[PDB]
Image: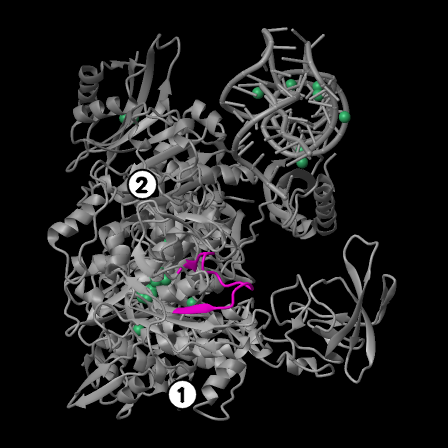
Amino acid sequence: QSNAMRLPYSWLREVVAVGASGWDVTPGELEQTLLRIGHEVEEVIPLGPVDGPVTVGRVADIEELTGYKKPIRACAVDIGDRQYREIICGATNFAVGDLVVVALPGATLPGGFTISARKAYGRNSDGMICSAAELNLGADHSGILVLPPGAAEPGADGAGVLGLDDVVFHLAITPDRGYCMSVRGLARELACAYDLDFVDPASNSRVPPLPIEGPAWPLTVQPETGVRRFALRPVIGIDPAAVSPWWLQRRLLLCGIRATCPAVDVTNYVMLELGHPMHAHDRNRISGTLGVRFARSGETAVTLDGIERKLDTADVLIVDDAATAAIGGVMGAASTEVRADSTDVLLEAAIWDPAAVSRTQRRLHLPSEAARRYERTVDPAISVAALDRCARLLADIAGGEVSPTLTDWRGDPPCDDWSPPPIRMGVDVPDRIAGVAYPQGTTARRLAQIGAVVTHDGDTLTVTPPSWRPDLRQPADLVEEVLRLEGLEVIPSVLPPAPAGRGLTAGQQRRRTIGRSLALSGYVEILPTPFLPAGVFDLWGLEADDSRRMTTRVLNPLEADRPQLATTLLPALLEALVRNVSRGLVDVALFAIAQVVQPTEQTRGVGLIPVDRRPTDDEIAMLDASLPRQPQHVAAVLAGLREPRGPWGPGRPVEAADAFEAVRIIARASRVDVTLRPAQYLPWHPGRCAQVFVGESSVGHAGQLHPAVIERSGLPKGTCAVELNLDAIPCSAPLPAPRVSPYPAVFQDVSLVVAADIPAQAVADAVRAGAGDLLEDIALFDVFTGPQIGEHRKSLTFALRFRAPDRTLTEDDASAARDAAVQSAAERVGAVLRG
Amino acid sequence: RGLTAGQQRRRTIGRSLALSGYVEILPTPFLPAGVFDLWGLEADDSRRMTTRVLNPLEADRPQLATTLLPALLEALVRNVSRGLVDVALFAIAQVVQPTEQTRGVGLIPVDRRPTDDEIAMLDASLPRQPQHVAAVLAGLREPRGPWGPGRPVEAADAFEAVRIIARASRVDVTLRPAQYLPWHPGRCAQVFVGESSVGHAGQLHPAVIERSGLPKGTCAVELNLDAIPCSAPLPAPRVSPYPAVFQDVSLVVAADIPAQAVADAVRAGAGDLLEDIALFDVFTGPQIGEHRKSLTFALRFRAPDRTLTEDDASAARDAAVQSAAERVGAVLRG
Amino acid sequence: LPSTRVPAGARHPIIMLAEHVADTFIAMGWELAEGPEVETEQFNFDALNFPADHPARGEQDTFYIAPEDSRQLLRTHTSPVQIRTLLARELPVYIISIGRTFRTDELDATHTPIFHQVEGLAVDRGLSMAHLRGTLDAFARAEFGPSARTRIRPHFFPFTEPSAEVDVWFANKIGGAAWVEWGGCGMVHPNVLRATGIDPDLYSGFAFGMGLERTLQFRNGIPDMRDMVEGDVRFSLPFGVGA
Amino acid sequence: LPSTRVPAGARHPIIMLAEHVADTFIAMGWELAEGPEVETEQFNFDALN
RNA sequence: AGGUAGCUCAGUCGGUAUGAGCGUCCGCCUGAAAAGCGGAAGGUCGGCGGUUCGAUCCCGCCCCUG
Ligand SMILES: N[C@@H](Cc1ccccc1)C(=O)O
Ligand SMILES: [Mg+2]
Ligand SMILES: [Mg+2]
Ligand SMILES: [Mg+2]
Ligand SMILES: [Mg+2]
Ligand SMILES: [Mg+2]
Ligand SMILES: [Mg+2]
Ligand SMILES: [Mg+2]
Ligand SMILES: [Mg+2]
Ligand SMILES: [Mg+2]
Ligand SMILES: [Mg+2]
Ligand SMILES: [Mg+2]
Ligand SMILES: [Mg+2]
């Protein structure tokens, strides 16, 4: 979690109470205040609680019990007043006299764990020595909690020595507030919320700056690496045996940082307090002058963890005469690493280019507490301040001597001002944006609390944001500061009057009609995944040059074997059909209305277009033309029983004609006419497949799927499918004016014999073309083959309804029209009147 | 705020009936002459209490419709007489039903806003004008084609039109036997939503059909939309991914025990493991016995957290059989 | 006896929720805008004021499209329709957009890599945060009832300044009436206006975006989001035909 | 071959014209109001001046 | 440690896949079902390769799950 920020409430209150003595607030109210100003509190963790005899003790002896597999030891502990207890433990991270926390019988630990005197192993175990995890204090259960020397005398209450009345807040800081990645930032924000005086913990008013009488180390810097400031200050003669005190290790642990040697513990404590990442180097291991430079084409380098990493030409690293020292603000190597062997250190305080750090730490796949903050910009004005704070805190704990020499690099031009350029903004600009009339002077006061100096000049403010707020660049940024501090809840709710809209487009309206029509006809909509099943087109047996194989590919799919984006909706539908069938739902009709992705040769990437102006019309056309074609398709699949069984009969299985009807349902919903012509197009059955035309434009296919496809894909037998390209179906806005004659109709039937492969629709069209205007309706109701007809023939019988517009049609008039239809079918499809 | 729930429902019912083959007509409010005498209605039938127009265009048709069926049946006869004999029509329109409280209100002064009691007076004085939905069917419900000879209109097609309207209204509906002219007394259901009657459906009475010159077997449905309550459900369906167990049960009951009552008894005993129940066979014959019938249901059992075993499903099936035995006297088929 | 020879189907509940959302804004005079699912990085990120080589962009859960240098992707949100609308239409603009969005989140009970968002955009003379709040309240009252209220609190998005998150309060909720996180919103960033040729000193605007699967989850009480995306007919059919 | 076993019906053209008219005004922020067909002379004439 | 019929599982440690259960199909039963008996169909034994005259078995690499 790169945006996380953990810290104890006691540390926050301490920094805030310096400027406002006696400030204290409940954790619930503090949570609501942080949320009101825009800080997500992900979790509020109170420490403990403990009850009963939970006191700090001193181990008197450790008679190691041998013979077992695990190193079990018996320990005598003094709980104060020289009243010794007998406890048994299996931890091996403490020696005689180390300070530990014990839980005597009668005590209770988090949570619901009452300590009792139980017999275990060869001795009596009336109590136990607790770990950080068992006390709800840390996240380490591998070893027992051992306090640093001199934390508290034996007998003190454990709830007070550990501060189990404290609460630790876990916050998720938005990426524009990197200054809140510290106690300095968060404490400043609270002073703004409660209108309190704030003393900056990185201010020189706390302690005077340490003296500078000369450079601390030879240092050359390349200008194009992007580093804005680099500081060095040595601390000579540290005691390796000395460790960090309890108040420092406690706060460090509560912030998620494990303590190691005191030279590194101060670098992490200062980083958490002020926000400036701190790195400790071993001055004894430094050889020659230090240099900041880009890497070579293949210059590898090992880190402190021993992993060598191939660097890029854009990586910023520090390197001396020997080998590489560290990788910018990512991580340091093992060359200058501080160990128990070290005694002389050289602390570094550097601001690195955020973009450079972001690229390197992301490509090398290793974030860090330092990298997360450098990615979000660090206040360069406090480099030496945090350095002097870090050197003084180190010499105080390890018993060293702060060297009065300091190296500082402020760029090729010695930058003295670290504040962003000033911003001009009208005084009432926050008022107009918020819709609230703020009291006089609210904007200037709020912008002062965040650290900006403002100068009034009529109705225009000149705001110079502080150096820790590089996000404040435009008047809009300043507006956000005023509104979030005043509270967004004061903003009223007025409904804006929108002009007369035009409603839904014809395409949006058609998408609804198709959904309603298919749903009413028994189809269940699914949301189709765009990631194709693995090897679906090979299961379909598609040719190598089938256009559907030309898929767009995702570099980082959730499933490695499914990176291709769907060029057709059928695989997703068939996947959902198999899912339903495998769950016992075998009579299923599904549909989907979604776009596909069809790249062409013109599909490619477009380089960044400047965003300081509107892109040109050719640039807009470039971006549109570069994307794969994404037309809207409608598709459906059917398996099992189309009509269920009931008291009416055994139901009816799905047939290819049901897919043909789904086409006509879509056509009717689209108010277009449609013709179906025979076609061979996988994955459809070559003898049960229609290609769908609107006019002379193909728009899709329908019918029963190929039996070989069905078996290879594990589909139900007889599965049918339809897929149409909605964008190929033209929009129609007809204005019918039907002729409704009230005169009687004449009913006649005609039986026509044709070759068995003459489509019935062609015969009907020929009949219609000859019958003329008197023909009102024609309907095929019988298709017959047999010995009465002849080989390779079939007989079609149509019901004809004739009607005149101005008179009662006579039988002779209708028969003349029928004979003309028979003549037409004879000339066009070779029909013969049935005899 | 857009369309009200009632306006939106009126559209959904129109779309649903139109997609199911029904053609909407605009029904005339002037009743055909002597229509209720053709129906053989009793003298005290509430439908005879009509509002009357003083100056109708046709002297013999001054009464305003208390039901939508006469107008629909008139349009059905018009289509049939013009050679269009396979016809399904529907209408969504108000009727006019005066009460004893229906009377005239004298002129209220218009130099000021009328009082609240004056507004209530004017509203209360008008005849009740509830919105009804109605439909009629004659001839072939499914036409003939290369698939087969088609299927004639049956009373079950009117029952399905009820369920189409119920689904469009997002309400559950029960059909109970009833005798209510002009419907066939043996092929007529009264439609309930909860315990509230909302209309009738089925095949029209053969005597009504002959006296009215209607096609044989004509069916009809009429519902009072305003009696159907509005529903805004928020479903959260249980979707178990575990395998289902399929079992069939064949139950013998008396011939006049409604199949829905047997299914409800089976469902009540099967418990939560029962996911779906479907009747697929109704059988009578010498193998069963006189005055009896045999119903066979397909049962699909499924557990929410485990693969259901055959024994677990059979225990649920046996409990359903016991429930149907106690409630409708069902006997397991042997 | 059972009479349904043609069993009813069902439009998807997410689609029906989208339709109700669409109808709500159409009845307020707004219109529906559209955009493709495979989108350029120009519109998904750059024109929306996302910084480059920065965690606010690189740590987005983005599906990138081959090749490496293509700057093509499955859109992580419907906000690129803001750019497309402002480039295609004359001011003033009052639109919503509803479509699929893609994140690299594993499918589980509360996450789905493919979901739907409703985007809102209003650009006009004199628009303020109060108009944003009036629209959210009307939006909430239409999707959750007359007792629905909205809460707004500061947040961050690169394309809004100020930025906020929208919480919703509706009666008959889960464990009683309480605040549920609903979506994000804010005033349109002036860099977004300048990237489309709009004078920020003359025109202002607000935008918002809510996920439909999330909305359907806490409104209806759907425990497992897998049921919303797997296409089991048992999940859809109880919602009705949707005609 | 013909495949439509359930022939399509039709909502009335006047009703559909009404629906389009309604949708037009709804998209402008207007709403639909209703009233009975059998009306008092008070509202049909007198209150209308 | 294992991968074995469509699924779920035993076996076979170089020269006829020994087998079950479910499922599927098929007969008995039922007007037709379910359930039950009865029988049948059903196995390059994980891919890629060696070794060998010959590999489910032994050797190399890799997919897969706990
Ligand atoms: N685009 C944001 C939501 C958002 C839209 C518009 C303005 C602010 C926020 C998301 O996908 O989460
Ligand atoms: Mg959030
Ligand atoms: Mg800001
Ligand atoms: Mg004739
Ligand atoms: Mg004749
Ligand atoms: Mg079974
Ligand atoms: Mg079985
Ligand atoms: Mg990313
Ligand atoms: Mg063995
Ligand atoms: Mg065997
Ligand atoms: Mg065998
Ligand atoms: Mg067999
Ligand atoms: Mg086989």
- Is label 2 in a helix, a strand or a loop? helix
> Of callouts 1 and 2, which one flags the residue occurring earlier in the amino acid sequence?
1
Query: Which of the 4 quarters of the picture holds residue B222?
Result: bottom left
The reply to whether the magenta stretch includes residue C60 is: no
* Residue segment shown in magenta: A330-348
Q: Nearer the viewer, residue A19 or B12?
A: A19
Residue at image coords 53%, 51%: B189
Residue holding disc 2: A666
Residue holding disc 1: A199
Q: Nearer the viewer, residue C210 or C21?
A: C210
Q: Chain of mark 1?
A: A
Q: Which of pointers 1 and 2 indicates the residue nearer the eye?
A: 1
Q: Tell how many labels.
A: 2
Query: Which of the 4 quarters of the picture holds residue E33?
Result: top right
**What kind of secondary structure does the magenta stretch mostly adopt?**
loop
Identify residue type, mark 1: Val
Residue B134 in percent (x, y) is at 40, 54
